[PDB]
Amino acid sequence: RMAEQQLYIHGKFVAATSGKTFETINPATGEVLATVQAAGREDVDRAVKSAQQGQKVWAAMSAMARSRILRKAVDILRERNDELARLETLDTGKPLSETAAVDIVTGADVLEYYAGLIPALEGSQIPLRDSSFVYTRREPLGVVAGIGAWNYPIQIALWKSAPALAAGNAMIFKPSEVTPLTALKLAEIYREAGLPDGVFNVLPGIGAETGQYLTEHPDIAKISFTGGVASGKKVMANSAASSLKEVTMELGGKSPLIIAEDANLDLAADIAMMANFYSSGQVCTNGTRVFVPAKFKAEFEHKILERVGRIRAGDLFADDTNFGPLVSFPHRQNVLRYIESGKSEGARLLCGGDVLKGEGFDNGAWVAPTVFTDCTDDMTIVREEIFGPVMSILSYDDEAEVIRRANATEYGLAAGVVTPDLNRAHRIIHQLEAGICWINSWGESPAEMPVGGYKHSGIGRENGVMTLQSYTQVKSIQVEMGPFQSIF
Amino acid sequence: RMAEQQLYIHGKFVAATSGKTFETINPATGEVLATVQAAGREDVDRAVKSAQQGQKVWAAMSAMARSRILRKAVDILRERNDELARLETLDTGKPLSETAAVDIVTGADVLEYYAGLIPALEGSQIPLRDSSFVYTRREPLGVVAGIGAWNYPIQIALWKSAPALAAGNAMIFKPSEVTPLTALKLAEIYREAGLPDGVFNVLPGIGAETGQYLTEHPDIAKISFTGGVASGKKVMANSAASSLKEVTMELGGKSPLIIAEDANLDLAADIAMMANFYSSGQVCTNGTRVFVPAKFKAEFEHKILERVGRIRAGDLFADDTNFGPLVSFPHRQNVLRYIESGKSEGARLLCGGDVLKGEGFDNGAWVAPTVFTDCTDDMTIVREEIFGPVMSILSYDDEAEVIRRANATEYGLAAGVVTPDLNRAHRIIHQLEAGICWINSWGESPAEMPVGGYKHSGIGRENGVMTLQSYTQVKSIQVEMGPFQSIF
Amino acid sequence: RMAEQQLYIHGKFVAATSGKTFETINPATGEVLATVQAAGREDVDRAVKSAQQGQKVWAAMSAMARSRILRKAVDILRERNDELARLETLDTGKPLSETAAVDIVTGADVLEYYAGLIPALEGSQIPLRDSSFVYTRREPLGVVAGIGAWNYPIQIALWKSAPALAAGNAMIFKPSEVTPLTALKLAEIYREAGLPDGVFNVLPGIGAETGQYLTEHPDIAKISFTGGVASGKKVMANSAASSLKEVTMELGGKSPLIIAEDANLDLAADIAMMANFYSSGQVCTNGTRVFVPAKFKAEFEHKILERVGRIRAGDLFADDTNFGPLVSFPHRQNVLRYIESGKSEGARLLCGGDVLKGEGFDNGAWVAPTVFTDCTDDMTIVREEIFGPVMSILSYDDEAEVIRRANATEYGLAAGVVTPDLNRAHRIIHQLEAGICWINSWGESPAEMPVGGYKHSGIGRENGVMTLQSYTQVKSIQVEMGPFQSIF
Amino acid sequence: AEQQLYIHGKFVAATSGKTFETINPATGEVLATVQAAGREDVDRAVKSAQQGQKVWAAMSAMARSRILRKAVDILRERNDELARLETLDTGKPLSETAAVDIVTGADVLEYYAGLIPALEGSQIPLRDSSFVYTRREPLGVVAGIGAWNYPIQIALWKSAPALAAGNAMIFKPSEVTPLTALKLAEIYREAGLPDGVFNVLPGIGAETGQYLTEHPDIAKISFTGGVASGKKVMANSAASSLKEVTMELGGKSPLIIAEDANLDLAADIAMMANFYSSGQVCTNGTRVFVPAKFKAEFEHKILERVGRIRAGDLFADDTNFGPLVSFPHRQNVLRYIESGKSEGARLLCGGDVLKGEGFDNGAWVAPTVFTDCTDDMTIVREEIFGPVMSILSYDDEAEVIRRANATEYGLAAGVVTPDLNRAHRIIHQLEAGICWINSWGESPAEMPVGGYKHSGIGRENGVMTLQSYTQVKSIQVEMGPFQSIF
Ligand SMILES: Nc1ncnc2c1ncn2[C@@H]1O[C@H](COP(=O)(O)O)[C@@H](O)[C@H]1O
Ligand SMILES: Nc1ncnc2c1ncn2[C@@H]1O[C@H](COP(=O)(O)O)[C@@H](O)[C@H]1O
Ligand SMILES: Nc1ncnc2c1ncn2[C@@H]1O[C@H](COP(=O)(O)O)[C@@H](O)[C@H]1O
Ligand SMILES: Nc1ncnc2c1ncn2[C@@H]1O[C@H](COP(=O)(O)O)[C@@H](O)[C@H]1O
Ligand code: NA
Ligand code: NA
Ligand code: NA
Ligand code: NA
């Protein structure tokens, strides 16, 4: 068990003044990983005043001075990749085979990416006439807040903090209460890299309290939130009610994976497996509606069954473990309710559908990888995000039908198509209503690539050059060198 | 009085099914200008279904085909400038000297600007490796909604609809109930120009009902709102509780004009006049806090008194008239309550402070140009936006103080400085917390120049190239040409 | 018979002072179309002084004022498309079925495109520190010179003049002695649209005299040249020996068309036909090396021969004529010399290979559509550009081989691939060393698409936003608001 | 020790059989003998670069970035060592070389390293059934030809964008100052740069430079030097394979002192614009335009400033003035100084070589200021490239602008004024690519720099220069049915 975890405000760990605490569990064992202090309303105010003071120092440095500090943090993250991944595995229940290859690697990639773009952040100059011209500045917002989710804790902390800090802001980050531990380590890493005190503060807490105090605080200029749709609506209401903040939201989806009639079904099955069962299905971009041509549906079902039999649950630190428990018992209960609705609504259970039992599983919230087929667009498991290891296989006859059904949803996060045909790939992808589209692949999210949702799946974008700009605000300045004329 | 005005949906005027109507008044005479039908909850759904159909046609056209249509609308607007300005004067009370020279001219300037940029709206391509690359599409949002304010009715309708249409969207526009007439004329002009049916629909109504139905509709992807802070908080809240929509907001301000000790006080007085009394002070960007060095205050007050003396109120269609009534009698009552708060807190009344009386004024919502001096930061008239012809003059001693006091507000819309000194002009402007900054001028808003507020004065920007992009959404597409590797 | 054509300098036609003239021939009949005056050194000097005066007026105008003038020119060009095309057909010998559908249509498209972009021409602003910043201006170069080629006379004049004028420069344009007539008409159109006098001047003449005087003139800031490699080298030499001009060149190519093993051979044949025999083969981008898999070559040859037999030479104004004479009789001799080298080097003539004879052809510079097969990479007709209707079909065995052979040339202008396979199309195209690449098509050159040559086929680019910027020069301006510190 | 060529990640003997010497300008002694790359050597470097460029371009963008940042870290750690070698080769005080030459060279490499992942093409929809996308592809093999005033900085400013864009560069340093370019090649290899990506071929411009400009497989030339040498480069590149050329030439930059200017500030700016690096800097404000009403005061102030100049041991901390790059170069500067007297200019100071212990053996020229200068004197119209300030008087703003602009040069310009309108108004009318307001000489990596008119072609630094080391490929994907008219 670990020592009690404190708040991180202004370059040092510090006790919360709320008097309150919470515990984070190891979802593989049910054991208390650490007791964690919760930030109260006065603690948030202290963090904002720390952040305001740090931000001025940060913004007054040269662009390359900021770049060098963030690249030093990258170097630390590269060195401690395996140690940080192990803590993430303990806190989240995700296999080490995942956390050591993706979570910190792709989080540091984004920090590294933005560190190098700081000197390229530029305004514009616009001539109006010989006697007047306009120039613009891309100024920091000031203090921004990030609210993280529990499925990719440190990756989210890096994907939010990297552009915010690169744009010259200070960020106060509130990790999920399920998974607060890696965010505290990152705050330590930033200071070791030379980040000025206050520029990145971490306030663990419950959403109902610490999160709400951040969304309500009048001196926070922007909120960036990744999480469930319900917690988002609350953040957006309390942020609307309070000071007028720009909000960015990354929510879930029910993303379609469209298998074309000319597609290799081994490739299609491999893509479908990776689009549904990575991180035990707890991934917003997962391709949970798999559309397969009727003529190949049966063969595809067998290929899935063959691959699902290969999934290896077990010791999360073992190299060959590729499947972990869900993050908590309440989350598994919701997944189990969706599975039962699939059975009751007439979907055909192809495999899985039950909790896992036996030594090593009775203490964690394990669900067997599950596949439903013979699914219809009106079934609950097809219409709603489950956030668990549950694939829905749907049959289709023609391209116009599958495009219509793929788009017939309020979600809009991701989509994909499998096809070797040049025209089919681009033609279909261009008609899909989704922000992240993969052709003959799934899941890769390069730092260069803006990612985010259409419709109800999010507001704004992360990664790419545009996200650096979105953590600045434009000031337009007109220089009038001619004589001003008044009509009064 | 005009025939009962109807909704404009899908290329034609159509009766509302709400059974509700409202009236718009001429603020110069108290007369009813017209009865106007109010869009019901079902009418909004019809407009959305019309906009969905029109947007598909509009987005399928070539970029240059959309450009030519918008440029045709521009040509119609220029030809009908004088006719449109008169209707605007009748509806708003603004002098024809303003409406004929600014409102349609600057509205059409923005439509003309965006018409030419449509073909330059481009995505990006990013190589990842020999075997994979990414490209992005800037796709239309789909159906967007604009909610207009009453101070610049047709200019606002153009500033919202021009980028929205240029980006490939359809807009449903709800004008302010105080000034609904010019937006309906704009819709006929767009159709006459060749805009497909459904791409620009106008639904008059009330904010509590019609505005809310638009902000609640699940198939509207973005809301752009211009108005008061209070209604903006409501819009953001209802849109949050409802479909997760992109939001843009242009709210009020309490913008500071910083007169420097080396400023020509004649130039400063002329800038202060234009920043406070154009459109009878009903302009969000107005410089309603005028900071003057103590050593120059008495002389500046004298020069202000001189410029107020030249103000020429009267018949709104006379060429020499340069001051009009407020937009409505209820708004005048609010402005009078601010004036009484200024007297009761001890601000010195320099001029004005009362309604205008006599033939041709006793029937209009006239307020005399009003200047308070000896003003202090804590006064209500200095802290709150009045949106009337009320200038507040505040004395300051040194630059650091005036920067702090200028910035010590929840508003963030505009700011300005009067100084011949190179270093002073840029140094001050760079430290001011405002999105729109004028050096030795006020009020000019070129189509090329992004405009919008810091802090509580707004979210997002209007005009400039960036606003065309903000009416698109980014779709990232990864083409994987290498073998896909599954870990299962 | 037309009247003698004069020089066009400063908004009017004016007599040359060279005392020298030349004739332009109708290539379908041999008759003299018109006598044209040649500009001497003093004529060029007068043109520069005219251009210098007009550029200042043109650049002092607002961006939108420049945009409206160019769009007015577009409107006249659309109205006069048929009349201009008929003149181009008379001067060049290209069928009206081409000139009325392409030459002015796509010329005006580029002018229309750049007209709308003028207001988006923007500099940048870079904050160095609190006390110093940099901003940049994109200023006009001043007076630039364009030297046109004879195959697309008015299109080239528009593609060069449109970005030059839109960037605020004046252009002196020198048309080819073969095709001077439409350039003089374009000058009249610009004046009628409102272009200031001197901003577009046209100086017919010969390359060795008029062309050299322009390339040598000290007050010309940039040269844009389209033509043969030998003439280009002369331009580059005189420009270096003289004042330090920027040169842009669009020279010839020997562009490969790669037919993949999975391509439909009817599509491949249609693309190859359009890539070789449009404008009688007189196109720099033509796909004159057609690479076909060995196993499909015989079937491809049959499809080519069937299509070549459909080619309709005849009256260039007849609707169904789709093949014209070469631009001149000296050019036909060069093409016939190449055809004889193909025969003598052992290439197999599949069709054509001789002049056309009979009523209607005997007086024209006609060459039959010619196809060689069994070609090898060492043959003269394969290594050198012919600029006539001569296709070379080359067999290949594998993808790596065809990429090497496609790239094994000093030319680098265009290339294309025919394949329905997603991976093959992008993978091959990414390895081809050419600036213009077509997948499953040929010849389309949208205004938005930058076009130009790799290696010896050109310097710089035309069209796209980047070409507007290339007709400006960057001025960087640092504003230092802090104290300057000298080490001396 | 006989310095050799650097090709494919190792030092290699030249196959020319020719050599040259570089002199320490402070002592007249030979610093080192350097081998000169011949015609076979140029073909070798190009063939090596072609092989290396594919490895380099095949890496990820971040892989290239990390290698370039490792080179930066080595350069910082070796700043003092490299600066000393630069001082020996150029005669610039260590106080300069340790603070500017490598510092500002590395800054540009560091800047471009971070931008590699942001180098992006474009995507343009044409219609539902067709779209276009563009790739920004490496040119391949490019060549840089450096000047002698800032040897390593020029090598970094040329090689950084070239390598960042995915090209290999062959760099030919000036024969006057070839030594630091070879250390840089070593540093790049140590940082992990693939072999062949940065090859260095010392030699003579008449031979080695020509062989680079004539080689058919070099896609672009970037040249910094004098106008005459540039015209030769451009001719040979014209007569040869069709190359993109970039040139950064000299200037006769004006420094305009306004009526409301503080003359202490103006004098400081004028000192740094004329006498830094002993006045051998292309952006130097050699024409200092001063109001007649202030000329006498400014002259006093110049004499006050010129008196603090401390010539001496180039490794001494307080030294701020060095010898010229070579004794032959000194004769040309002295030839210009004699022309001001013959042309009637009043010599306010300097104008001779320096003498005594420690100066008789160096290529010293005294800091020189002429006043009573006229627009027609040779020293006012032509670049001297030595420590010679020309003071010119003016009466009205239009005159100084036209006179400032009345030149074929267009490199830099500056104005000294506290007035908002005059700075922007004057600067917007000056025909120069590099304009400083109330300062001089600062050249941030972010700021594009280059000449108007005869002072250069193209630009260096800034994001645009990264793109200019790429070539655009446009690709149309036609998904509709293709229609032939035959
Ligand atoms: N009402 C709320 N206000 C602010 N943050 C919240 C709220 N409810 C939950 N959160 C936080 O939002 C993130 C995601 O929530 P969930 O989707 O419920 O896991 C976690 O950091 C929660 O603690
Ligand atoms: N609650 C609301 N929801 C939507 N629109 C509203 C709401 N309240 C006011 N509006 C509209 O917002 C615009 C400006 O609001 P106001 O500042 O109140 O005049 C007008 O078009 C109003 O009708
Ligand atoms: N030496 C030259 N200098 C300038 N322009 C030339 C020269 N030779 C030919 N031209 C022109 O270049 C264009 C195309 O050259 P060509 O390839 O010979 O048709 C025509 O306008 C020629 O008149
Ligand atoms: N004709 C030439 N061709 C190529 N490079 C040259 C030529 N002349 C001089 N150079 C080189 O150009 C650089 C600067 O030239 P300079 O202005 O003479 O010092 C040095 O590297 C010279 O060796
Ligand atoms: Na946990
Ligand atoms: Na009204
Ligand atoms: Na002709
Ligand atoms: Na030397």
Image (cartoon, coloured by chain):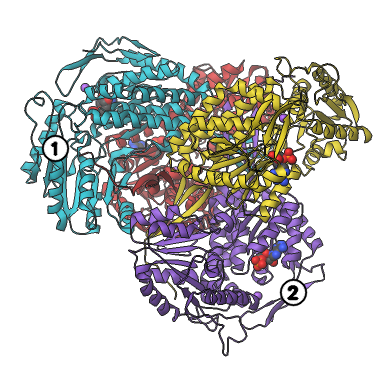
Chain colours: A purple, B yellow, C cyan, D red
A168 vs C73, nearest the viewer: C73
Q: Amino acid under label 2?
A: Phe
Q: Residues within 10 Å of mark 2 (few under 14, many from 20)?
A: some
Q: Quadrant of residue D54?
A: bottom left
Q: Amino acid at mark 1?
A: Pro
The residue singled out by tag 1 in the image is C369
Q: Secondary structure at mark 1?
A: loop
Residue A179 image offset from top left, x and y in percent: 65, 71
Q: Are marks 2 and 1 in contact (CB under 8 Å)?
A: no
Question: The disc numbered 2 marks a residue on which chain?
Answer: A
Residue at point 62% right, 54% down? B244
B180 horizontally vs D101: left or right: right
Q: Is residue B48 above or below residue A150?
A: above
According to the image, label 2 marks what residue? Answer: A22
Q: Please report, as a chain letter, where disc 1 is located.
A: C
Image coordinates of residue A382 in percent, x first then y, are 52, 67
